[PDB]
Image: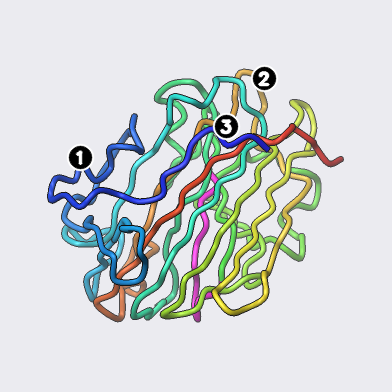
Amino acid sequence: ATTVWSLSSVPHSSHVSTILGHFKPIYHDWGDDSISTSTKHSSSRALRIFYEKGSYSKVHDHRGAGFYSRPSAISSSVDAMILKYDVYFENFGFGIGGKLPGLFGGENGEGAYKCSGGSNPSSCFSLRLMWRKDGDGELYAYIPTNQESGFKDRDDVIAHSTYGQSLGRGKFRFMNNKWHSISEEVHINTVGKTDGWVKICVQAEGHSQQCYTANHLRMRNTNSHHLRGMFFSTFFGGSEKSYAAPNDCYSYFKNFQILTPSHAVVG
């Protein structure tokens, strides 16, 4: 597969706009106060996100960070994409869950950035990861309501009426105080079919790779929708205090890559 974009490290800068420079263009960025850089766990200077004890999505300060990234090298009709990155969890403390970066797509414009929170218009899909209780991982998908028959009753699905769908929860798990290599391979559906899929592999250093494949997915209902790039998103929650971070804790990200393999749907 062809690598169209990568980001090994971030510069040692106090200016967040410079820290995030090679992610650009970015859209709907937030969380400056949580963003810094660190070589504590790696030779490559990593993007570091701070989550203050007690923080979650609704807390005003130090609750994490978010932005959509659409590197210019990505063409406008990409139907298959692989996102890779390394993440270190420091002092987790996973509480009852939070967000991690994943891919997103949809319309070519602002419509693509609307699939989060309580919002799921027919302009986008988003495929962030989440951690959960005890560091269990999942695909956390904002996808169209018209999924295949019986979708909600799938063994790999914990559905929600308004928020994201939990796919594959517990099939991989995140470990405190370790690096993890993460890959998310996404092939969006043929329009008119539920033949899209997502394969996530996670490997904590020292341990065996664990992979989960979500197949028979619908991401789009129209042919003008495509994969657009990375939805960088990380914070605890959830929308209420029960999701508050139990600890002052930190995540570190390095070695970002986006590849574009040949599109291959699975019916």
Observer-side mark, 1 or 2, equals 1
| 191 magenta-colored | no
Instruction: Quadrant for the N terminus, please.
Output: top right
Disc 3 versus disc 1: distance between alpha carbons? 25 Å
Residue 103 lies, in percent from the top left, at 53, 43
Residue 99 lies, in percent from the top left, at 43, 59
Disc 1 versus disc 2: distance between alpha carbons? 34 Å
Q: Give the label on residue 223, or none.
A: 2
Q: Which amino acid is tagged 3?
A: Leu
Instruction: Quadrant for the C terminus, please.
Output: top right
Tell me: 44 left or right of 129: left
Q: Earlier in the sequence, mark 3 or mark 1?
A: 1
Asked whether the residues under the numbered discs 1 and 2 touch, taking CB atoms below 8 Å apart as contact, a structural biologist would say no
Q: Which amino acid is tagged 1?
A: Ser
Q: Which residues are magenta?
A: 126-136
- Please tell me how crowded label 1 is: few (under 14), some (14-19), or many (20+) other residues with Cα within 10 Å: few
Label 3, on which residue?
Answer: 227
- Name the one closer to the observer, 252 or 172: 252
Q: Is residue 89 above or below residue 25?
A: below
**Label 2 element class:** loop
Residue found at x 63% / y 70%: 172
- Please tell me how crowded label 2 is: few (under 14), some (14-19), or many (20+) other residues with Cα within 10 Å: some
Residue 235 lies, in percent from the top left, at 34, 61
Residue found at x 56% / y 46%: 83
Q: Which amino acid is tagged 2?
A: Asn
> Residue 205 occupies which quadrant of the picture?
bottom right
Q: Earlier in the sequence, mark 1 or mark 2?
A: 1
Residue found at x 26% / y 63%: 38
**Label 1 element class:** helix
Q: Is residue 160 above or below residue 5?
A: below
Label 1, on which residue?
Answer: 17
